[PDB]
Amino acid sequence: KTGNGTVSVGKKGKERQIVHVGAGEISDTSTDAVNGSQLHALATVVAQNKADIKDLDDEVGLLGEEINSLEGEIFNNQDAIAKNQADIKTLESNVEEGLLDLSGRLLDQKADIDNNINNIYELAQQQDQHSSDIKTLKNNVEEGLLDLSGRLIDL
Amino acid sequence: TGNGTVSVGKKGKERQIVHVGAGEISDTSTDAVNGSQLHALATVVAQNKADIKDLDDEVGLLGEEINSLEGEIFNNQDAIAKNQADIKTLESNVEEGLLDLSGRLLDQKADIDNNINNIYELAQQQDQHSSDIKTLKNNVEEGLLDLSGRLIDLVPR
Amino acid sequence: KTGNGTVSVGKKGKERQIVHVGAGEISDTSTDAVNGSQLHALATVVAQNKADIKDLDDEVGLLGEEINSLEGEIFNNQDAIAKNQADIKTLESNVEEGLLDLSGRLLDQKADIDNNINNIYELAQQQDQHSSDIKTLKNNVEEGLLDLSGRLIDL
Ligand SMILES: [Cl-]
Ligand SMILES: [Cl-]
Ligand SMILES: [Cl-]
Ligand SMILES: [Cl-]
Ligand SMILES: [Zn+2]
Ligand SMILES: [Zn+2]
């Protein structure tokens, strides 16, 4: 067997195929030759591993895009929340201011209701002193007129 | 075995080529290769296959995590919309409750100010009645006194 | 060499390389020997698949971290949303309590104003009667005085 470290089936630039080769053992100790059908079988797996890596890559890109979409929506939630927070605060201000000035107009109106009840009391006093001054006057015109009348009939 | 090919057998009676030393594995190698070299590669391809299947599972779990998040985000959207709507409902209840009270409070404003025009009309009509009583009692005293003074009739000196 | 199931190019421990082997047919029926550049081409693809699987594992690991950080924004939004739910119900009750209290004040002012109307009316009726009593008393003492002197010039 030619060449003493090597068995040659041609020369550089004039290579030969080796044909009618039985398939060899495929193991970590095999020193059998390998034929093309054995490389083909392996290449079929590799192709399938490659097609599968491509499908996973497409999947992983879309997952990443969905995560970014979800992030966009979390941030719209945040804005909406801040806006509700702000509208609560302005609605807080508008409640007490409005009730504050409803309460100021209640106190002004009680002040003049209290003044009106005072005047009604005072008017009611001097209205009863009048009902007496008018009946003591009425009695003393009667007494007086008929005392004078009495000194007329004395004649 | 011409000068295109070399044959170790025939169809149906192929032969294994045995005691083959490992050949150079490079992009110009014209060496035969042996079965432990193909074995070495096939082990890597097995490992890659196994690793793709682990990776697939992780991708599957990630997808389930993402849909969990989506579900919570949707719950946040709902509650936010319920808050948004309670706030408008409260804002419209507060406008109608203040305006109804400010309306009853200004119908009182007006009816009280009419009571003050009436207390002023009573107070100075009552102040004429006081001076009418005085000038009435004065003219009574003055009119009886001058009748009594018409005793001049009966005057035994 | 030939041992009828095998062709030998060496022996155990003194195996030889076959050289100047032209590329065999790669196909599922092929009985061509394969050479080193044919296995090298395939291993190149296996290396790329291995590189791709690692990159993808790294990408999938960053998305897992991304997802985790978003979880934390979601639970913060839930805190904020809950705070807002409380503040709104707290504000609802303050608004109800505040406008109920102001309503009480307005009814007790309405009470003392229609009493003021009842009393201002009563005063006016008692006051227009005084206008009655003062004018009749006037022309009743006018009538009394002028008949006493009507009779006292009868002398
Ligand atoms: Cl959210
Ligand atoms: Cl692979
Ligand atoms: Cl909210
Ligand atoms: Cl009043
Ligand atoms: Zn990508
Ligand atoms: Zn064998």
Image (cartoon, coloured by chain):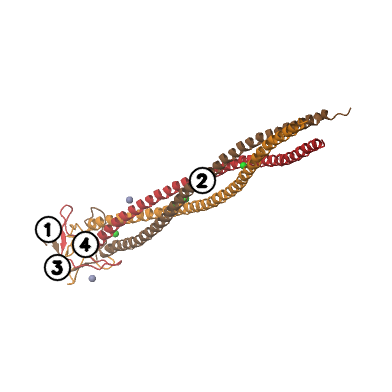
Chain colours: A red, B brown, C orange
Q: Residues within 10 Å of mark 4 (few under 14, many from 20)?
A: some
Q: Which mark is residue B9?
A: 3
Q: Residues within 10 Å of mark 2 (few under 14, many from 20)?
A: few
Q: Residues within 10 Å of mark 3 (few under 14, many from 20)?
A: many
Q: Relative to residue B113, is residue A59 depicted above or below?
A: below
Task: Say whether marks 3 and 4 touch (CB < 8 Å).
Answer: no
N-terminal of the pair, mark 3 or mark 2, is: 3
Q: Which residue is mark 1?
A: B4
Q: Name the subunit of mark 4.
A: A
Same chain for the residues under marks 2 and 1 in the image: yes
- In the rendered structure, which amino acid carries the disc numbered 1? Gly
Q: Relative to residue C153, is residue B97 depicted above or below?
A: below
Q: Nearer the viewer, residue A15 or C52?
A: C52
- In the rendered structure, which amino acid carries the disc numbered 3? Gly
- In the rendered structure, which amino acid carries the disc numbered 4? His
- Rendered location of residue A27, percent (x, y): 29, 67
Q: Nearer the viewer, residue B128 or A145?
A: A145
Task: Say whether marks 2 and 1 touch (CB < 8 Å).
Answer: no
Q: Which mark is residue A40?
A: 4
- In the rendered structure, which amino acid carries the disc numbered 2? Asp
